[PDB]
Structure formats: structure tokens, C-alpha cells
Image (cartoon, coloured by chain):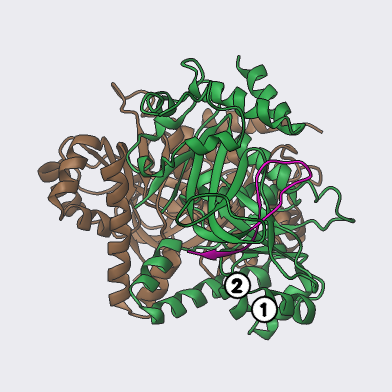
Chain colours: A brown, B green
Amino acid sequence: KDYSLEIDAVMKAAQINDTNNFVQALMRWHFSKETGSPFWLGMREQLNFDPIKDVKTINDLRQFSDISHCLRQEPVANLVPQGLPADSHPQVYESGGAPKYVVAYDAWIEALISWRMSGYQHRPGRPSGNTLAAIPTGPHIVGAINKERALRLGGMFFSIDIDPRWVKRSLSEGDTATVRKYTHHLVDQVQNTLMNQDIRFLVTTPPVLRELLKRPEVVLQMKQSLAQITLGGTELNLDEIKFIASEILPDCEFSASYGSTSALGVSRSLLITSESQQVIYDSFSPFITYDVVDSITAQTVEYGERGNVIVTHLSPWAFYPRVAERDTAIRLPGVSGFAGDRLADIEPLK
Amino acid sequence: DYSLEIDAVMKAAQINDTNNFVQALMRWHFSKETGSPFWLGMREQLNFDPIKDVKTINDLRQFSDISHCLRQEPVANLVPQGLPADSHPQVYESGAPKYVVAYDAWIEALISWRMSGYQHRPGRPSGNTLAAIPTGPHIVGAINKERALRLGGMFFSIDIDPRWVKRSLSEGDTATVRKYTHHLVDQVQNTLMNQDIRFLVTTPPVLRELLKRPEVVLQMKQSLAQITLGGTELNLDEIKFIASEILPDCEFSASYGSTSALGVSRSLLITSESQQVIYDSFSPFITYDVVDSITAQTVEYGERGNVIVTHLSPWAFYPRVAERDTAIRLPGVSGFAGDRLADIEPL
């Protein structure tokens, strides 16, 4: 059976901002016997409400509980909605790892990157070239997302070896000496590719950039080559980035990327300039939506306040409601007329 | 366009028409219309004519190993113009370091070859693959992803930094090597215990430690149809012991990665009667010669020599690469060009 039309109808509602009809169509999608995943079909009777009857809007998803705990041992094939084309091809990705297993699909990553890059498509005399993504691949969805982006930027995708779990383990054991040497190891790989191939775009993190900038010869190269630097993670220093953007690489654009593997995605910051007072992120609403909640009371904070980040993914490919992330952010109003909060100045839970 | 030209090279290979395969691809690689910028701009400084002075696989000996080019050559230059515009090159690396490009049609071809037995192998298992091997810039990741797709389940990976391991043992820092190895074991254990894994791809040092955890042993006995072991430091006695005493219902084989040749070679199934680990290549696209360390002449069957590998296909051309391995030279063949290898060892 072909549900191509049904999927298309869903993606159309999202594009139009018909967010209420989007949600209702995907409740039907996820909980009907023909099109849903074994996982959500099996979960239905244990919910304390009827997802088809009682969920009409994005706000109504607050009735769901975070089911992240199920994701260590739930067989990954149970995550696959029956409604998806035989051609889909699920790919397995992981977070927490320890660890949670999720499935993602090319059509989803393609849709997400078309949203993410939608502005690059309009901005004047867009740069093109190779991307060096100094980011995890293996079980990490960020790798797959960055590979799709590099495709749109009209060059090839260059990668490095980087084990983020090893870095984490070392830090947690307070082995500062290992973390230190590992960082220099990462820097050396990034240096090699930048010095030996023509790289137009770089995706990295502040500690690796910091070290790269200490070397005049790499600086000279980046100055000539790099159109864009994307910085990822939750340990971004705005004043320092603003310093690099004006004093060191004034011809390079700087942006931040905030990854939510639980929501199968990434959120895109506004460009960081001398005018920037916060780093401000938008999500791919209505597919990925955020709520920002008080650390003590679990109620949505006032705009401008910091609270805990709660992310929800809903799409033809997956459904992960109300996931408590271990990050905090300033809550800001969505622009665009779309549901979901905008986030600023992400930090780790302290 | 060039569709029928490529399809014909593939038919040449399919029916083992070796001479016309080499010839047609010398034309392919050295035409101004279909060639790659790299091999076109390389032609003049050759002491021969690839179109005239090459008839056979053996003739490729006149070529030198261009691997030292591959650091700074723009990867765009390795792309044959003849490839359909809809192709999509991916970059892979080896050694500080060499860049090459590879294509899905190629990896798909290699895997259809590798898995040809998995048709004619009795009532085959299907399920998920855990490939505890490098991804990132490493082609071995992509190849294993394609294999998993054929086996009827999903591809699970781990984080593993092969360059860090190499950097660490090179610094004589064996505390880090031990710690890092168990970090790998820990990740493999988590997936084996939490998800249903049918096929495992790993290395002897990781597998050795996995087997020292009783729960993981029981899980592997219950779930694993196959283990593939990679690298050039196989201990055949050890593997045979594991196959008969510990994992009696799991099939063992070895994989020899030829990154320079954008491929892997598969060993025969390892059994209690195995006396050698014996590898076959995807001939005629990937072919081995085993040569003398001083003279560079092909050794005798049964003798250990330096491994030399050549890739030739519509997607690429990499002649006479000196690999950093030795092997016993063995007769190829159910007709095919190229040597069989046994018992690879590092140089």
C-alpha cells in the first residue's frame, strides 16, 4: 500500500503552518493499526488519555510523558512506522552513551536540511565549496545531518576521527591530561585537512577552534578559505566568538548549531555579529518544538527567563514527546507565527 | 551517455574477459572525454602509453604507485568525467593522510561480490549488524554499512578513533591503549546486550576482552550467527579455539581492508581444519601481486612477499600500491586474474 499521498498532506500542513491539522494527522498516523509503529501502537493502551481524541494542537502534546527510558531496550525495528515506504531504509542513531537507540531516515534528514538552509538559498552570492565537519559520525545523527548539509553547499564532505564518548568519559573521571592531549589530536587532524585541501566551511567546537587560532599559519589559511564557521555544543562564549568574528576572521560568517539527537535534529542560530546580544536559536517547527520550564516548578517560564529545555519531535518518521534534555536556555517568543519557543544562550544543567 | 560504455566494462568483468576489461578502462581513464583530470595530467610524464603499451593486468606493472600524490591533489581531480553527473563522490582517507574518492555504485558492486555466497549458503541468517569499526573518513565504514543492508537488518556502530589508538601506542603509552580498548569493549557490550545483534564485525583485541565477560559470552552464544575479524594481527589458533569451544554456533571469517584499492578482501570460513587464513579479492577490479622486498619481482606460490594492490574500475585507477603488509602468495582462481593471499602480517 502506498501512503505517499498521506505523508505529502502532512508535510504540506507543516509548510503552510497548519499546525493543528499537522498534529491531528500525525496522531492518526502514529496510532492507527495500518500506518503506526509497533512501539507507539503498543504504548497506546498505557496512555492516560486517547491520543486521537484528546490531542488537537502542539500545546496538547504536553499530555504525553517522556518515553526516552524505553529507548535502551526497545528493539529498533519497533520504531518504524508501518506507513513509511518499503524504500525508506532506517538508519540507527544513539544518544546518552547509556545509550538510547533511535531510527532516522534520509527523507527526514533531507527535509530538515532544506528547512535549515532555506535562507542560504536566498542570501546574495552564496558561497560554495567543501565542508570539513570536525564532528562525530558513527552512531551520531549530527554526522548524517552535516553530510546532507555539505551536499547542499556544493562541495564534498570531509570528516575527522573524533570519539565524543571518550572525551566525556575522560572528563568525568577528571582526567584533564587525557582531555588535553585528545584535543590537540583533534586540532592536528583539522589542521591537516585545512592545510592540504580547499575548505570553504568548517563545523567545530570552541576548544578546537581556540587551539587552531593560536597558529599563525592556519589563521592565514582560514582567512583566505573559510566562508563559514559553525560552532556546536552548549559551551559557547558570545563575547569570545564576537572577538574572533571581528578581530580575526572578519570575512567569515559565524553561526551556532544546537543538536537534539532525542528530536532527531539540529536547531539553527541567527548569524553572530557585532550586534549580537544573545545567541538565538530557531527549531524546525512544527516537527521539532521546544518548551522551556522552571527548574523548580516545571511550569513554562516567562519570556526572558532561563529554564530547562523540553523538546518534542513529531513527523511522519517518528514521535518523541516532551523529552527532558539536560540543557537550560532563555525562553524567547517564536517568530514566524509557528508554535514552539525560540531559545537563547544554551547551557548545560549545572 | 557513457552508460553503455560503463555497463560493457562491467560485463567484461562479469564473464572474466580480463584483457578487454583492462584495455577498455585504460581508454576510459585516459580519454579526454571520460578520464579524470588527475590521470589526464599524469599521462605525459609516463615512460609509456597506457592505451598502446597495456594489454593485460600484468602490463600494469609499468605504472608507478602514485600514493604520495594523494595528500594535496584536489579530490575533485580524481573524478572521471565519464561518470554520470548524478553520481556523488564521497571522500575517504588512509595514512598525514591520503584522500581518495568513492561511489555508491562501486561499493554496491563490491558487496554484491562479497555476498555472492550469502545466496548459496544454506538457509542464511538475517538480522542486525554491529560493526565495531571506524566510520568518519574510513571507507571500511561505508563498505560495512552496505553489507549490513543486505543482511536484512540495521547497521549499528560505535565510536572508535583508529588514529588515536595508533598515536597512543606510537607514544609507548600502553595505559591509554588498555583504557581505550576497554572503552571500545564497553560500547560493544552495551549494544550486544540491549539490541538483537546477528552479525558482529570487530578485531581480536576487542573480542578477547569481550569473551572475559560471562554475560556477554552468553549473549553472543545466543545471538551471533557470524563474527568477522579485521586487521593484520590474526592468531589462527586463538580464533579456532573460540570457534570450537566458546562460540560453537557462530561462523568466523576474516576481512582484509585494502583502502588504497577502495575495497576489502574476504577470507574463507575459519574451521577446526584451517591451517591458513586465505583471502580472495574482487577480481578484476581489485588484484594482488606478492613481490620481493629488494627485487620487486613476484615471489613463488608458497613464499612470503610484500603485498601490492591495484584498483582498476570505471570509478578509479590506483596501480601497484605498495601496502605495508606481507602475505603468502597463493594461486588465484576459478579463472580470475590476481593472487590469493594467506596469513597477512605487518611489514
Does the magenta run of residues contain B181? no
Q: Residue at x 35, y 45 (%)?
A: A281
Mark 2 / mark 1, whichever is N-terminal: 2
Does the magenta run of residues contain B333? yes
Label 1 sits on what residue type? Glu
Check disc 1: other Cα within 10 Å, few if <14, some if 14-19, many if 20+. few
Foreground of the two, B67 or B297: B297
What range is drawn magenta here?
B329-347
Foreground of the two, B162 or B343: B343
Residue A53, can we see it?
A: no
Circles 2, 1 touching at the beta carbon (< 8 Å): yes
Label 2 sits on what residue type? Pro
Check disc 2: other Cα within 10 Å, few if <14, some if 14-19, many if 20+. some
x and y percentages locating residue B281 in the rendered image = 66, 48
x and y percentages locating residue A259 in the rendered image = 43, 52
Chain name for mark 2: B
Chain name for mark 1: B
Residue B238, numbered label:
1
Residue B5, numbered label:
none
Vertical comparison of A29 with A329: above or below: above
Foreground of the two, B22 or B237: B22
Foreground of the two, B81 or A276: B81
Relative to B303, A202 lies left or right: left
x and y percentages locating residue B152 in the rendered image = 76, 51
Question: Mark 2 and mark 1, same subunit?
Answer: yes
